[PDB]
Image (cartoon, rainbow, N blue to C red):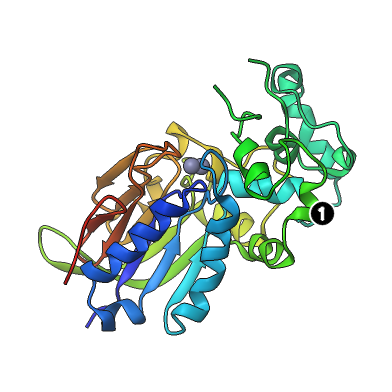
C-alpha cells in the first residue's frame, strides 16, 4: 500500500483550526495509514491569528504523539521573519553582514517603520520588517506580527519577546527547512495511480534560473538574500518551472491565499491567515481535501 502524505496549509496562529484539522484527518484516514504518514507542514505558523505560541506547542508535541509519522516543517516567509527577529538565522555563508540585506528595500523603511530597538543592527531585513510599526488594518507590522508578540505575552515590537519565546520554540524555528524533497510519492491522476518526485517549498520555485541551483540555496539556507522569492513570491512562483514541467514532480506550496490544484502543482492555502477561512490539508494519493470546518467520523 502507498504511504499516506498529508500536506498542511498555512496555520497563522489559529490553534483551533490546526486542532480541528488534525482531528478531522484522523477520521478521513484509517488509523494504520495515519500512524505511518508523511506529514508536511507548508509553513507560516505565526502572525495574523491569536495563538502562535499554542500552535508551536502543538507542532512540537507531534513526534511524541505519533512516533511512526515523519514530520516536515517548512519555513514560511512569516516564520523566517520571526526567526530573524529572534536572531536565530546563521550569518550569511558568503561572509556578508545581515545588515547588507537592508539596502535593496531601504525606501520602504519609513512606511513600514522598521524595528530600531535593541539588536536591530545585526538583524536580517525581514526580522526588522516583521517587528516594525506600519503607518496606518495591519496587526502592528506589515507581517501582522502583533498577535505573535501577544500570544507570547509581550506588546508588539518588544525586544522582550526574545526572552518570552521558550528554548523549545527557538529549537523548532532552527529546525524548519526551506525545502523538502521526496524521491517517491503516490498521487492519483485521471489515468490512474502514479509514482512521482515531490518538492515542498512554501511559495514555489522560480522560472529561468536552473532548478538544482535554486534547490541548493534552499537546502543550505542562504541568509544573504534580502527577500527569498521561494518563500515570499507571488506570480513568479505560481507555476511549475520549465525543467520540472514534465508530469514527474509534485510541487506543493502554501502561501498564496488560495486552494489551487492544477495537475502536479498543489497550492494549499485556503486559510490565507484569515480568521473566517478554513485551514485545508491535501491527502495523497487520493488528493482529497480535508478542512478544520469538516465534521468527520469513521
Ligand atoms: Zn501565509
Ligand atoms: Zn507565506
Does residue 25 appear left or right of residue 236 in this picture?
left
62 and 237: which is toward the camera? 62
Q: Position of residue 95 (x, y in %)?
A: 86, 51
Asked whether residue 239 is in view, the answer is yes
* Residue 243 falls left or right of residue 170: left
Residue 281 lies, in percent from the top left, at 33, 56
**Screen quadrant of the C terminus:** bottom left
Q: Nearer the viewer, residue 105 or 130?
A: 130
Residue 170 percent coordinates (x, y): 71, 61
Residue sitting at 36 percent across and 37 percent down?
276
Residue at left offset 27%, top offset 84%? 32
Q: Residue furthest left?
A: 191
- Quadrant the N terminus occupies: bottom left
Q: Residue 87: in sight, yes or no?
A: no
**Which residue does the image show at 10% across and 62% down from the upper left?**
191
Image x and y of residue 126, in percent: 70, 38
Q: Nearer the viewer, residue 178 or 145?
A: 145
What is the count of numbered marks?
1
| Label 1 Cα neighbours within 10 Å, binned few <14 / some 14-19 / many ≥20 | some
**Mark 1 Cβ inside 8 Å of ligand 2:** no
Position above or below: 70 against 197: below
For label 1, the residue is 91
Task: Say above or below: 44 vs 285.
Answer: above
- Is residue 186 found left or right of 44 in the rendered image? left
Q: Is residue 68 above or below residue 92?
A: below
**SS at circle 1:** loop
Q: Residue at x 21, y 57 (%)?
A: 295
Amino acid at each position: 500500500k502507498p504511504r499516506t502524505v498529508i500536506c498542511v496549509g498555512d496555520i497563522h496562529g489559529y490553534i483551533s483550526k490546526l486542532n480541528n484539522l488534525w482531528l478531522n484527518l484522523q477520521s478521513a484516514i484509517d488509523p494504520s495509514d495515519f500512524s505511518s504518514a508523511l506529514v508536511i507542514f507548508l509553513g507560516d505558523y505565526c502572525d495574523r491569528g491569536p495563538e502562535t505560541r499554542k500552535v508551536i506547542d502543538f507542532l512540537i508535541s507531534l513526534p511524541e504523539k505519533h512516533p511512526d509519522q515523519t514530520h516536515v516543517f517548512l519555513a514560511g516567509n512569516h516564520d523566517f521573519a520571526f526567526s530573524g527577529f529572534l536572531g536565530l538565522l546563521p550569518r550569511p555563508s558568503d561572509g556578508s553582514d545581515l545588515k547588507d540585506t537592508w539596502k535593496e528595500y531601504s525606501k520602504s523603511e519609513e512606511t513600514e517603520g522598521w524595528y530600531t530597538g535593541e539588536g536591530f543592527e545585526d538583524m536580517h531585513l525581514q526580522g526588522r520588517r516583521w517587528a516594525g510599526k506600519i503607518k496606518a488594518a495591519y496587526k502592528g507590522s506589515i507581517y501582522d506580527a502583533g498577535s505573535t508578540f501577544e500570544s507570547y505575552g509581550v506588546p508588539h515590537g518588544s525586544s522582550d519577546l526574545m526572552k518570552a519565546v521558550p528554548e523549545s520554540h527557538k529549537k523548532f524555528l532552527t529546525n524548519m527547512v526551506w525545502v523538502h524533497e521526496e524521491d517517491d510519492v503516490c498521487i492519483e491522476t485521471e489515468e490512474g495511480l502514479k509514482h512521482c518526485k515531490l518538492i515542498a517549498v512554501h511559495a514555489g520555485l522560480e522560472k529561468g534560473n536552473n532548478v538544482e541551483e535554486q534547490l541548493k540555496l534552499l537546502r543550505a539556507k542562504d541568509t544573504s538574500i534580502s527577500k527569498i522569492q521561494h518563500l515570499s513570491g507571488r506570480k513568479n512562483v505560481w507555476d511549475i518551472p520549465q525543467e520540472l514541467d514534465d508530469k514527474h514532480t509534485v510541487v506543493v506550496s502554501g502561501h498564496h491565499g488560495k486552494l489551487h490544484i492544477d495537475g502536479m502543482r498543489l497550492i494549499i492555502d485556503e486559510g490565507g491567515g484569515f480568521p473566517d477561512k478554513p485551514v485545508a490539508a491535501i491527502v495523497l494519493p487520493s488528493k482529497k481535501i480535508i478542512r478544520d470546518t469538516d465534521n468527520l467520523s469513521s
